[PDB]
């Protein structure tokens, strides 16, 4: 037979069902008598392993792969090779932790995943990015900064273990804070391992003769690894190869000295030449490649991967060889060796045969072609036989009919109904049956009306955290799910710049610590001892421009900043006891500051604070100092409006917990400033003016190519993919209805 | 210097890798007496006891042949207060140093801060 | 530009062939291949017939190589069959058969060629240069094994970081202040230099000399500015300029502003009041001082360190990357091409060129329009001369749309200037007779429509066979091309896109509904057929507009397929989705990451489901249990079975198929699962796979392997294709909605018009911008030509007066900047009326126009059809038997896994972990534990000279080569003599009295057993006939059948009376009293070594009954002798040794028990 297929995965999935059909049809057949001859086992082992491990219990037949490359304990073997690649390394934290992730190397120093989870965030937040030591820095011909290194990180961790982080620097290194309790033994184990690595990389540098190269492999294995019930075979194989190569070099009477990079790259190449073939005739189905000088008679022979350009396997002569130019009888070549192996594989089969190959690409549905040997076999089969239907029609037409009858073009996807239609090419799978019979139900909508009642005590901080961002607070407050992204992988570079999210978070921390108008030199020295600012002049420039901006801002801050007090609010509104504390409250009014740009969210937080203050006393203006001529302004109001609007906000809160309240304040603030003015107190109704307001709203929603928009967010992406006209009209109307609080409150 | 002695003491299972690496880090290339004092300070702070008499650290001879260990400078510098003040990493407690000597006992800076704050809150 | 026929082309020297669109390039190549393989042409033929492996063809892409190979093989087979039969039907085959004289010789040559075809050279440029380098490695200076790599982004990042740390840290504050506003950091440096880091080095115009230092440039700028500062300091104190009233009265304020400005020179930018004292400022609105011209001398030249630092970085980073890759031993495609170019250009190039030219004395460079200067230099250097060697270039200059790939058109222009021969093709085998005339009328308007000199458009003609092509829509016929025109005066991009997508979708559904009833017929002559959903295919040029037209077309209820995305799968949502799922299933104990995976969009839950999962605790417990089970399935059997079980349990495959717009997500899910399995097999851990996934999400590359597959093909859908990957395909009906959109090139990168050499400019000269914009317009014209010519029967498109100027409307449009506008308006700007009348000028019997108006009637009529019912097949009997081959591993339990498969001769029976027990004295009891010392002690004794005494130098050499410390020699050299002289069994003792004729080491046996061995039935006879079987833990085995395996250590004889000897090294018996006849007897039962007794005695008996005739067990056997290597004193008899003898009836019973 011949089976044209699309992908290797689909080839092996077809072969499994065909083998099962043959085994069920023939009452006298054994898995001992079936062979599958892949052209190269390295590219077909994962798919075969996956499907033959995923076959269920009532459909299972045993299997055994042979003739792989001589690496089975891959973590141990590549870990050992990476240990031999020490003096050329750069010692990044991800590589060092990759050595820790090996279970044998982790259990050597008696640390588990319960400690590894601590050491991940320890090395992430402690500032350990670059190499091990100043010598390692200098051997790469780079300026020895002495900061953000392994020695720096371990000194910082142990100094933070000894002394609290509020005592400042002692030897120009700020102490760390978390590693203080009964958890520092993991840090000690890591430090001991790092010391061992430093000693061995110092010992691995200089060239040695063979007589001195003799014991270093055994010393390395015993010093680093730990023998187990299984790894000892791999250790014995490694020792045997190392001993064999060095003993041959010694016996060949070599007297000079050799570098380590020669023996390492020779061992790593002699490892990948042996094979393992002691599971060949064990009883399961025999999976093996095409090897010469081996022709065992079997019952069913299956060949996979007969693509053009894959078989016969090619190997070029060395060029300066002399047997190529002058051939004779006894010469042997890989091409004719494989060409004769095909004939032996055709002769050795006794009962059936099964040839499969990719015939169509799965990416673009293009055309591919089989090998020349398969083409010649099919041509001879077509030219030697004829179907009994057309006894005398035509030679070429009969050939075409036979070649079309023998070939069986399989389907492209597993859940196609043609697989499960009754007939000859029926499948044995059952997990795709409801997906192929179209017997499922579609997805519903994520948001649903959830019954939420209002308790008698909501704290002020909960309301502030809700009204900072209502949709996100609904996600991480009512149903406690946040889409926290993957953890930030430890960067391979020191902090050069401060931009983007790094600007936001780190610069927010730096400015919020810098506001307090005290001595700046001590604070700058402490933050540079912490190892956050860039190196030298660039950090000085950044600190100076931040100082000359923030002193200008602090001038207008202190120009009216009379020191006030901090009071406490207890109040009963709608039968609810709102409690909270007040920062920066004074008899003058509301004067605040937050080192960021001007935003209606900030203005609305100030508005809430002003309303709760006016509900409990509270006469005075509402200002909050911001950058780029930042200003907020509204006169104080009366208790009637204060209580009315407070009740309206509490009702909005109790509705937004139950339902996904649509409030987009900044785009809504832009549409507020466009439509509603302080001179008309009525929205415009002209089509051109309303479309201009829509234009301002949409540019605030999604930005141009220069800047990013508010709507481009993970939460809004989760709610909907695109902004259809129906839902944007719904957004405008829901703004006009529920943002109408903010519409009236802020002008 | 004495790092192999500390390693074989760890092999004898009375000092921890945390203690020896901490002592090595905080002392650098200081005197043998200072390194052994730091190591025993780390061990006795890890066992729980905050007290650490000088007489005990000079007459214990438990984890090592400490007589032959402390005979590494000229003669036998028994003035442990002077040899402890001589090191730059240790002061009397005014400078921000991890090692504090206040009541004729050497203990860590964090314990000293906790004791001082709890004493001031008691009075 | 002569008419070309493949049967009369002279195959000598250099040639050049330009084939029009839809002409049969692959056909002409195959015809020339056959002609060269036969050596035909008469006076214009090659001197000798060549062979298969001496016809080099450099084909562009791998799919094209595969198709070319298939077409060549099929043509050779058909030509051989036709030459055998002497008759054919194909006209070219008839002409060739008339040309050939010797039919039998031709048949033999074609047969040999067809058999030789499995090694033919239809290759690419990289696959060619790689083999030529690996062949002439002596001339080229290369290694003999190179590991390829394609990740150069990290190398570029490390090189730029090293440059930043090398030439920006020693700089002082007053210079770091200068460079800071010039650029922020290495991120911006890479963002500015990445497009020029790779490829051919761009020739920098006006470069600084190499002697200049950045500090020297800073000092030069400082000198140039305080010169004019000193001149102003001299010139203050007078007002001698021209007094005018129309200016500002605060000119004296400006003078005082400059005068108080002269304090410091630390700044780099000058003040804004210096722009009104220049000669330009005086002539736009009286010399009297030389400062009047000195300020012009200052302001005539810009000031920047940008050019210097960019030159230094561009000259350093590439060499650093090359040096690091050379040091670590890797290779790449660009590196191979550059290395071949350098080796051919250098002094050793002559012998290399001779070898290549005598290896491949012909070449057909396919797709010549996409050519690099390096490849052209190589081809020129190899085949520019040395006659009786030919070269045939083939390419179409009008379809060179691969400028972003790295190709260049000016190299082709220089090649066209150099080559003195020109040929072209005229016929068109695909398009419509009205379509070719419409394209000719559209493109033959002006002179040199492609705005260059060496690209002349010529008319083409259709074939006489396709003269009956037509298209009828409800009766009357239809014109070929038909623009659709927006009504208005100004337009915007979003409204343009919306109205054109809606009009396109409306016309598509109208066509489909009018053709489903057999009314809209694609008539060809007298035949007829109705249209379907496969013929209609729009042509978009970008993914966002593809998605927009997809949403519009499914809003009018039409399914659609997207074909030719270039980006990878890893940039979509599914990659982050599986990253979250894998992060949750790796550590399912954390409630936060468990709930963050339970709320994910493909699981298909709701807020009520999350609420009822959060409040209840038993549901949470069983979710944690099932996720732990999934993690266990992962840790045992890889990634793909875990995901398959998860999908089959959580119904995701059916849910995403019942939900519309989810089959694409399912296909992407399967692709990411397959790629994850492929990577995780070759990786070593699980967190490494997670990091691999996250890193590939962070870096969405655009390689040739990680692209998007087409989602489905079961039902024909309308194909939204991309212009670039539509090159070479064919569709009956097309649509071009967004053809009147353009982009304005801004960066300075232009080619010189005299020498065709690429020139890089680092200044803001408008000449560079105009020269770049001209090339951009030419590229857009060629892309428009491709998109126009892909059609066959009909081609509609939409023209609108697009204006992107900041001002609203002034009357003049910028549509002449577009590829269609520059052609329609003949190059000059016009108005809407001029656009309409120049459209109406070309409305003559083949081209029509209409105003686009939106008409909504109905979505569609789907015509739902149900077919049948289906079922899955059943398995009705047991899959397999329990045949096995065991090597004494039934009794020793599992845990000893693939160790036996890795090392067959390993000391399996020794295990444990060592410690430190270092007593100062050395004793054999202190030999270290493990398997390596055991397999050393066992490997010591096979090859010895037992009769002769042992040599100490041999012991020292063995201990030195074994990786052991060489001080063990005096202890071992007496231990060997102690163990070699034991009194074993009162005869045959003291093994040194055994010759080499009486020994046989390391035997291997095989015992076939039928009648499956019940574990109880073996022990039920062992326990009776042996006192050591008091301790009874039996049935440690299961039912097994098949062979048996095992190793006998040594077997000898002493006047008959054979023996079985066994060395066993074991645990640290630190005292000699721990190896007595009671301790060993206890350990025998504690380790179950008693089975080896009966198994080995039966194996040796079954061999003696075959070898020795007239064999008696009692008269010939004698027993089995066990020893223990550790614990053999000098003179301590019967210590460490153990002797046992079987019962001589148990063997006779167990033999027939095994074999029947």
Image (cartoon, rainbow, N blue to C red):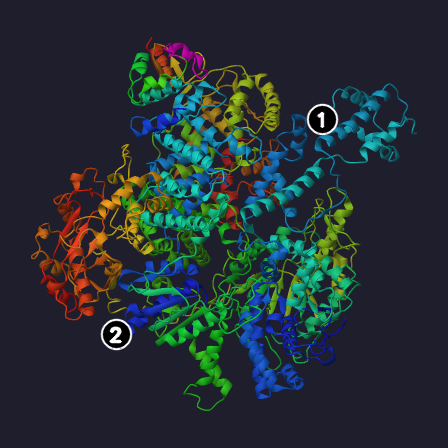
Specify the principal SS of the magenta part.
loop
Q: Nearer the viewer, residue A514 or A240?
A: A240
Mark 1 is surrounded, within 10 Å at the Cα level, by few (under 14), some (14 to 19) or many (20 or more) other residues, namely few
Q: Nearer the viewer, residue C388 or A102?
A: C388
Q: Quadrant of the N terminus of chain C?
A: bottom right
The residue sitting at the bottom extreme is A392
Q: Which residues are magenta?
A: B75-93
Q: Chain of mark 2?
A: A
Q: Nearer the viewer, residue A478 or B106?
A: B106
Image-based side of A628 in relation to C752, left or right: left
The answer to whether residue A114 is above or below residue C461 is: above
Q: Chain of mark 1?
A: C
Please give the name of the residue rendered at 92% of the width and 29% of the height, measured from the top-left corner: C287
Q: Which residue is mark 2?
A: A27
Q: Is residue A653 magenta?
A: no
In the rendered image, residue C231, in percent from the top left (x then y), is placed at 84, 24
Q: Which residue is mark 1?
A: C267
In the rendered image, residue A589, in percent from the top left (x then y), is placed at 52, 19
Of the two numbered discs 2 and 1 in the rendering, the one whose residue sits closer to the viewer: 2
Image-based side of C381 in relation to B62, left or right: right
SS for dot 2: loop
Image-based side of C237 in relation to A243, left or right: right
Numbered badge on residue A440 = none
Q: Is residue A601 visible?
A: no
In the rendered image, residue C529, in percent from the top left (x then y), is placed at 55, 77
In the rendered image, residue C708, in percent from the top left (x then y), is placed at 50, 57
């Amino acid at each position: 037979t011949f089976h044209v297929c699309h992908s290797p995965q689909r080839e092996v999935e077809v072969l499994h069902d065909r083998l099962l059909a043959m085994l069920e049809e023939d009452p006298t057949l054994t898995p001992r008598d079936i062979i599958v001859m892949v052209a190269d086992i390295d590219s077909y082992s994962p798919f075969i392993q996956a499907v033959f491990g995923s076959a269920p219990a009532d459909r299972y037949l045993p299997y055994a792969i042979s003739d792989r490359r001589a690496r089975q304990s891959h973590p141990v073997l590549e870990a050992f090779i990476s240990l031999l690649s020490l003096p050329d390394s750069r010692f990044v934290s991800e590589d060092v932790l990759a050595l820790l992730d090996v279970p044998v190397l982790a259990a050597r120093f008696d640390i588990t995943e319960e400690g590894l989870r601590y050491l991940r965030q320890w090395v992430n937040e402690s500032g350990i990015r670059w190499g091990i030591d100043d010598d390692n820095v200098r051997e790469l011909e780079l300026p020895a900064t002495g900061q953000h290194t392994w020695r720096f990180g371990l000194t910082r961790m142990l100094l933070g273990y000894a002394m609290e982080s509020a005592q400042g620097e002692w030897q120009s290194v700020l102490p760390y804070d978390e590693s203080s309790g009964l958890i520092a033994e993991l840090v000690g184990h890591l430090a001991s391992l790092l010391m061992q690595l430093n000693i061995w990389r110092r010992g691995l540098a200089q060239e040695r003769p063979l007589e001195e190269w003799l014991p270093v492999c055994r010393d390395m294995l015993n010093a680093f690894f730990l023998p187990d019930a299984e790894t000892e075979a791999a250790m014995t194989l490694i020792e045997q190869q190392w001993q064999a190569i060095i003993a041959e070099g010694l016996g060949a009477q070599y007297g000079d000295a050799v570098p380590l990079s020669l023996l390492r790259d020779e061992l790593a190449q002699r490892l990948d030449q042996e094979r393992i073939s002691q599971r060949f005739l064990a009883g399961p189905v025999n999976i093996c490649t095409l090897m010469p000088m081996r022709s065992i008679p079997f019952k069913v022979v299956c060949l996979l991967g007969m693509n053009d350009g894959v078989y016969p396997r090619q190997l070029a002569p060395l060029g300066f060889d002399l047997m190529s130019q002058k051939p004779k009888r006894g010469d042997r070549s890989r091409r004719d060796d494989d060409r004769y192996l095909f004939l032996e594989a055709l002769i050795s089969a006794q009962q059936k045969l099964y040839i499969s190959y990719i015939g169509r690409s799965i990416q673009d549905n293009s055309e591919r072609f089989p090998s020349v040997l398969v083409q010649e076999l099919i041509d001879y089969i077509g030219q030697s036989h004829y179907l009994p239907g057309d006894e005398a029609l035509n030679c070429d037409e009969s050939e075409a009919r036979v070649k079309a009858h023998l070939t069986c073009l399989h389907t492209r996807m597993p859940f196609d109904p043609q697989n499960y239609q009754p007939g000859e090419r029926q499948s044995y799978a059952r997990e795709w049956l409801p997906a192929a019979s179209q017997a499922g139900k579609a997805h519903s909508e994520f948001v649903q009306p959830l019954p939420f009642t209002l308790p008698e005590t909501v704290p002020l901080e909960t309301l502030q955290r809700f009204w900072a961002h209502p949709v996100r607070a609904f996600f991480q407050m009512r149903l406690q799910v946040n889409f926290r992204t993957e953890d930030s992988e430890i960067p391979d570079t020191e902090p050069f710049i401060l931009e983007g999210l790094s600007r936001y978070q780190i610069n927010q921390q730096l400015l919020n610590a810098l506001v307090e108008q005290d001595d700046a030199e001590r604070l700058f020295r402490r933050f540079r001892a912490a190892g956050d600012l860039p190196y030298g002049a660039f950090g000085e420039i950044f600190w100076e421009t931040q100082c000359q901006e923030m002193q200008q801002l602090a001038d207008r801050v202190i120009a009216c900043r009379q020191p006030g007090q901090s009071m406490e609010i207890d109040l009963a509104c709608n039968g609810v006891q709102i409690t909270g504390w007040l920062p920066q409250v004074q008899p003058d009014g509301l004067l605040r500051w937050r080192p960021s740009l001007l935003s209606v969210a900030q203005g609305m937080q100030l508005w809430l604070e002003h309303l709760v203050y006016c509900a409990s006393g509270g006469n005075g203006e509402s200002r909050l100092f911001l950058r780029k001529d930042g200003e907020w302004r509204f006169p104080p109001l009366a208790a009637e409006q204060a209580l009315h609007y407070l009740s309206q906000l509490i009702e909005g809160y109790r509705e937004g917990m139950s339902a996904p309240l649509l409030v987009l304040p900044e785009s809504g603030g832009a549409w507020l400033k466009t439509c509603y003015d302080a001179q008309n107190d009525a929205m415009l109704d002209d089509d051109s003016t309303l479309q201009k307001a829509r234009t301002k709203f949409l540019q605030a929603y999604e930005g141009n190519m220069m800047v990013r928009g508010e709507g481009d967010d993970i939460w809004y992406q989760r709610l909907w993919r695109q902004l259809t006209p129906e839902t944007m009209e719904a957004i405008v109307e829901q703004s006009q209805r529920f943002l109408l609080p903010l519409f009236r409150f802020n002008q | 210097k004495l790092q192999k002695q500390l390693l074989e003491a760890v092999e004898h299972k009375q000092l921890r890798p945390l203690d020896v690496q901490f002592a090595l880090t905080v002392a650098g290339d200081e005197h043998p007496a200072v390194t052994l004092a730091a190591a025993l300070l780390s061990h006795d702070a890890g066992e729980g006891h905050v007290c650490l008499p000088l007489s005990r650290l000079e007459n214990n001879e438990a984890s090592h042949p400490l007589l032959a260990t402390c005979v590494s400078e000229i003669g036998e510098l028994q003035n442990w207060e002077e040899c402890l003040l001589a090191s730059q990493a240790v002061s009397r407690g005014d400078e921000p140093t991890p090692m504090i000597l206040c009541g004729d006992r050497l203990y860590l800076n964090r314990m000293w801060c906790n004791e001082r704050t709890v004493a001031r809150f008691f009075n | 530009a002569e008419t070309l026929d493949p049967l009369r082309l002279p195959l000598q020297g250099e040639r050049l062939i330009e084939a029009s669109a839809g002409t049969g390039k692959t056909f002409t190549i195959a015809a020339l291949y056959l002609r060269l393989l036969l050596g035909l042409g008469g006076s214009a033929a090659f001197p000798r017939p060549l062979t298969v492996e001496e016809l080099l063809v450099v084909t562009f892409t791998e799919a094209a190589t595969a198709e070319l190979r298939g077409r060549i093989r099929s043509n050779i087979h058909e030509l051989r069959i036709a030459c055998l039969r002497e008759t054919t039907d194909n006209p070219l085959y008839e002409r060739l058969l008339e040309e050939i004289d010797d039919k039998a010789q031709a048949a033999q040559w074609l047969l040999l060629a067809e058999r030789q075809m499995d090694e033919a050279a239809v290759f690419t440029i990289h696959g060619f240069c790689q083999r030529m380098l690996n062949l002439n490695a002596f001339e080229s200076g290369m290694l003999f094994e190179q590991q390829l790599i394609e990740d150069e982004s990290l190398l570029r990042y490390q090189a730029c970081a090293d440059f930043w740390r090398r030439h920006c840290y020693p700089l002082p504050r007053e210079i770091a202040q200068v460079v800071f506003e010039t650029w922020k950091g290495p991120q911006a440096l890479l963002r500015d230099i990445n497009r020029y880091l790779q490829g051919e080095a761009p020739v920098i115009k006006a470069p600084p000399p190499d002697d200049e230092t950045l500090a020297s440039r800073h000092a030069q700028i400082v000198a140039r500015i305080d010169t004019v500062k000193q001149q102003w300091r001299d010139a203050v104190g007078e007002l001698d300029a021209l007094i005018e009233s129309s200016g500002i009265d605060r000119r004296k304020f400006n003078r005082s502003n400059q005068a108080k400005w002269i304090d410091k020179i630390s700044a780099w930018a000058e003040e804004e009041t210096n722009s009104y004292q220049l000669p330009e400022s005086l002539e736009k609105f009286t010399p009297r001082h030389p400062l009047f011209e000195a300020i012009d001398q200052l302001l005539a030249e810009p000031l920047s360190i940008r050019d210097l630092v960019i030159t230094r970085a561009l000259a350093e980073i590439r060499e650093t990357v090359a040096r690091e890759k050379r040091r670590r031993g890797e290779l790449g495609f660009d590196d191979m091409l550059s290395r071949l170019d350098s080796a051919l250009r250098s002094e050793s190039g002559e012998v290399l060129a001779a070898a290549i030219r005598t290896r491949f004395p012909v070449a057909m460079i396919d797709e010549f329009q996409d050519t690099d200067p390096q490849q052209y230099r190589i081809f020129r250097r190899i085949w520019h001369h040395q006659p009786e060697t030919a070269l045939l270039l083939i390419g179409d200059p009008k379809q060179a749309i691969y400028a972003f790939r790295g190709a260049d058109i000016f190299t082709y222009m220089k090649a066209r200037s150099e080559v003195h021969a020109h040929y072209t093709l005229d016929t068109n085998w695909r398009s419509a007779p009205g379509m070719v005339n419409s394209v000719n009328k559209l493109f033959s308007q002006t002179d040199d429509a492609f705005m260059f000199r060496e690209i002349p458009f010529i008319p083409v003609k259709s074939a006489g066979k396709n003269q009956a092509l037509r298209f009828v829509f409800k009766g009357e016929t239809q014109p070929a091309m038909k623009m659709w025109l927006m009504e208005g005066e100004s337009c915007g991009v979003g409204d343009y896109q919306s109205t054109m997508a809606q009009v396109c979708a409306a016309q598509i559904r109208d066509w489909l509904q009018a053709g489903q009833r057999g009314e809209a017929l694609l008539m060809n002559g007298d035949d007829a057929r109705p249209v379907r959903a496969s013929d209609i295919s729009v042509l978009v040029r970008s993914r966002q507009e593809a998605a927009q037209v997809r949403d519009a077309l499914t809003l009018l209820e039409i399914p659609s397929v997207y074909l030719s995305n270039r980006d990878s799968v890893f940039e979509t949502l599914e990659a982050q989705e599986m990253l979250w799922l894998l992060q949750a299933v790796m550590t399912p104990e954390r409630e936060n990451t468990l709930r963050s995976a339970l709320a994910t969009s493909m699981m298909g839950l709701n807020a009520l489901d999350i609420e009822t999962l959060n409040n209840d605790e038993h549901a949470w417990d069983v979710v944690v249990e099932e996720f732990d089970g999934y993690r266990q399935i992962w840790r045992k059997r890889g990634v793909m079975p875990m995901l398959r079980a998860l999908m089959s349990a959580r119904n995701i495959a059916e849910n995403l198929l019942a939900t519309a717009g989810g089959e694409r997500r399912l296909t992407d899910i399967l692709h990411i699962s397959e790629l994850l399995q492929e990577a995780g097999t070759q990786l070593e851990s699980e967190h490494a796979l997670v990091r691999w996934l996250s890193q590939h999400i962070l870096e969405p590359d655009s390689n040739a392997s990680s692209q998007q597959m087409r989602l489905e093909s079961d039902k024909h859908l309308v194909q939204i294709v991309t212009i670039h990957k539509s090159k070479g395909l064919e569709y009956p009906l097309v649509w071009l909605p967004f053809i009147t959109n353009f982009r304005v090139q801004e960066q300075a990168f232009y080619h010189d018009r005299h020498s065709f050499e690429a020139v890089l400019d680092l200044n803001a000269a408008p000449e560079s911008v105009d020269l770049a914009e001209a090339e951009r317009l030419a590229e857009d014209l060629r892309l428009l030509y491709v998109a126009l010519t892909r059609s066959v029967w009909h081609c509609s498109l939409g023209v609108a007066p697009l204006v992107r100027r900041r001002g609203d409307k002034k009357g003049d449009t910028d549509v002449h900047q577009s590829a269609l506008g520059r052609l329609l308006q003949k190059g000059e700007p016009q108005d809407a009326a001029g656009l309409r009348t120049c459209i109406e000028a070309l409305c003559d019997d083949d081209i029509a126009w209409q105003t686009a108006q939106t008409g909504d009637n109905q979505p569609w009529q789907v015509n739902d059809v149900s077919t049948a019912e289906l079922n899955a097949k059943t398995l009705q009997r047991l899959p397999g038997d329990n045949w096995r081959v065991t090597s004494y591993s039934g009794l020793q339990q599992r845990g000893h896994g693939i160790a036996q498969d890795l090392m067959p001769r390993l000391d399996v029976d020794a295990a444990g972990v060592a410690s430190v027990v270092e007593e100062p004295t050395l004793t054999p009891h202190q030999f270290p534990r493990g398997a390596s010392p055991g397999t050393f002690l066992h490997s010591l004794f096979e090859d010895l000279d037992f009769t002769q005494p042992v040599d100490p130098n041999w012991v020292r050499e063995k201990l030195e080569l074994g990786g052991f410390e060489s001080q063990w020699e005096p202890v071992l050299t007496e231990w060997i003599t102690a163990v070699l002289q034991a009194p074993l069994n009162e005869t045959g003792v003291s093994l040194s009295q055994l010759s080499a004729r009486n020994k046989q080491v390391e035997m291997e046996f095989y015992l076939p057993i039928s009648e499956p061995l019940i574990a109880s039935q073996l022990d039920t006879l062992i326990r009776q006939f042996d006192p050591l079987s008091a301790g009874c833990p039996p049935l440690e085995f299961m039912q097994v059948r098949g062979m048996l395996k095992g190793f006998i250590d040594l077997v000898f004889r002493h006047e008959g009376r054979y023996y079985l000897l066994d060395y066993k090294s074991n645990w640290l018996g630190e005292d000699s009293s721990a190896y007595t006849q009671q301790a060993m007897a206890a350990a025998m039962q504690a380790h179950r070594y008693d089975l080896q007794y009966q198994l080995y005695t039966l194996a040796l008996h079954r061999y003696l009954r075959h070898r020795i005739a007239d064999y008696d067990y009692e008269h010939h056997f004698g027993g089995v002798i066990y020893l223990f290597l550790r614990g053999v004193d000098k003179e301590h008899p019967q210590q460490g040794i153990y002797t046992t003898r079987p019962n001589a009836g148990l063997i006779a019973l167990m033999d027939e028990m095994f074999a029947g």
